Image 1 (spheres, one colour):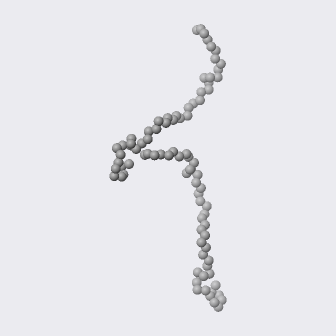
Image 2 (tube, chains in turn purple, blue):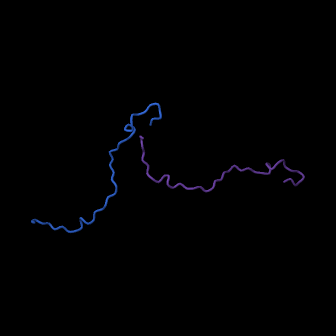
Image 3 (cartoon, each protein chain N blue to C red):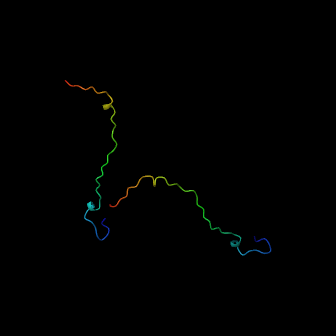
Length: 43
Length: 43
């Protein structure tokens, strides 16, 4: 806080680092896996 | 394939010939078979 008589060394001790991760909304999957699939065993 | 050290003679030995036979859609027949039939025994 750098305001009282006794301070702290650096902002690293005034800060809490979280370990959790957040992601935005993403595009959905639609046409990838709708058709039936024909297994193949040659060129 | 012609990428490795050993190859094959032609695509005929890299192919599968299937005996399965398939057909497209076909027109439906309506008029030939709704009128009553009159048998005859002379000209």
